[PDB]
Length: 50
Length: 50
Image (cartoon, rainbow over all chains, first blue to last red; front, side, top):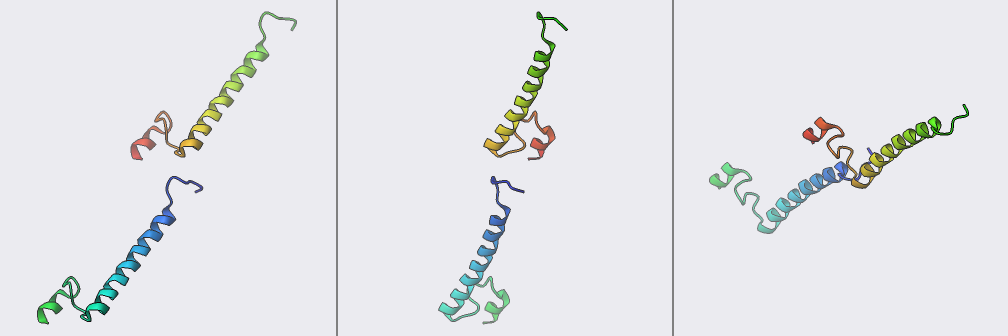
């Protein structure tokens, strides 16, 4: 469709950008802290064991 | 025939012109707003779904 009111492609690109940014954020946190398991939401049992 | 009081052809042309202008008005409104479903008289259930 040749409509301008809403751009589905832009929305999909925004979603994929957000996913990539979340991956970048978790990678950056794990690099800076040096700890894979911080903010227990990743590997919740792992943080208890550690 | 040779009648001048009433001009049937002019009336028919005016009616067709009115139909054309109504179509132009709907097209102009949809163009400016961008919404096909506007003025709920057009696509009544469509506006409910929207």
